[PDB]
Length: 31
Image (cartoon, rainbow, N blue to C red; front, side, top):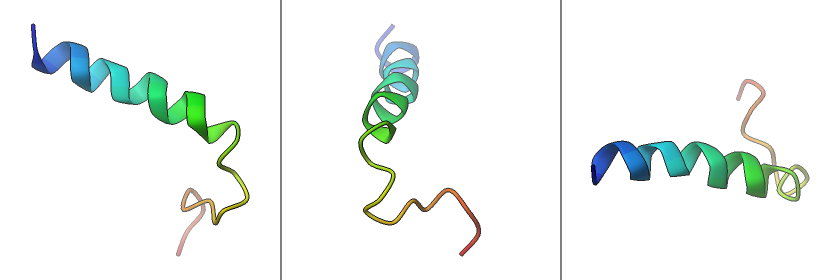
C-alpha cells in the first residue's frame, strides 16, 4: 500500500527522532 506504509513509517520516524528531540520543547506533556 501507499498509505499504510507511510502512516506506519511516521510512527518509526517520530519515535526514532524523538530520542534526540526531547529538549527542543517536547510537546508530549500537556500544553
